[PDB]
Amino acid sequence: FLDLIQEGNLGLIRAVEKFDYTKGYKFSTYATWWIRQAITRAMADQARTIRIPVHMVEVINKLARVQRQMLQDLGREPTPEELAKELDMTPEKVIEVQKYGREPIS
DNA sequence: CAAGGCACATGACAACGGTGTTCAGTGCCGCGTTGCCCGATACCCCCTACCCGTAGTTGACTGGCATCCGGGCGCCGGGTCGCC
């Protein structure tokens, strides 16, 4: 948690360095974007034991959230072909990213 | 009856027979190993597809988390604030 807080502080430093009153709005609304940017970047780059590239992180979390949405909607485990058409990629990519989306056991 | 004269064979005599050595010369032919000719190959090129890193995204949105008790048991050892 405090490590995330540190990273958000870095994102704030960036946003502050990249802010002025030329925008007719509060700093916080503008900042929330940079803060989430830095936090998501670090979560993609430093959270897992195995280092996963950013596009791979977004692929996995996108397929995960949409699969969860299918679980909530259908009330049943979506069949892999359904997931493949939903993500629009092939089942091969589905299994690839799924297996790439695990964590070690200590 | 004894001596002298003719047949057949006989002591050597070389020279062929046949074959065995030996010289001496030149090969014969055993294997070892060279010189070719091909097929494939690793190694340069070009092209685009896709992974991987970087940079933005403007209503507002200003302090979190769940801890933890039934060890148990004793000791050391230091700290810690009263004590007179």
Image (spheres, grey):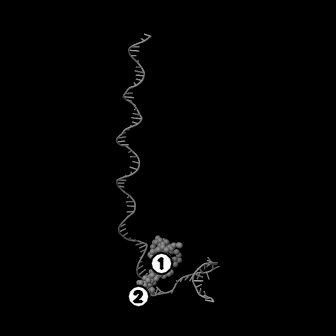
Q: In the structure shown, which secondary structural element does the residue marked by tag 1 occupy?
A: helix
Residue under label 2, please give it: A21
Image: A38 above or below B29: below
Whole-percent x, y for residue A98 in the image: 49, 73
Q: Nearer the viewer, residue A67 or B54?
A: B54
- Chain letter for mark 2, please: A
Q: Which residue is mark 1?
A: A43
**In the visual, does B29 lie left or right of A43?**
left
The total number of labels drawn is 2
Please tell me which residue is depicted at 46% across the width and 76% down the height of the picture.
Answer: A45
* Residue positioned 46% across, 82% down in the render: A9
Q: Amino acid at mark 1?
A: Met
- Picture quadrant where residue B17 is located: top left
Residue A70 pos. (x, y %): 50, 77
Residue A104 position within the rendered picture, expressed as x and y whole percent measured from the top left: 51, 73
Residue drawn at x 49%, y 75% is A48
Give the chain letter at badge 1.
A
> Dot 1, how many residues are within 10 Å of its Cα: few (below 14), some (14-19), or many (20+)?
some
Q: Tell if the residue under mark 2 belongs to the same chain as the one under mark 1.
A: yes
Q: Amino acid at mark 2?
A: Tyr
Q: Identify whether B48 is placed above or below B82.
A: above
Mark 2 surroundings: few (<14), some (14-19) or many (≥20) residues within 10 A: few
Q: Nearer the viewer, residue A90 or B63?
A: B63
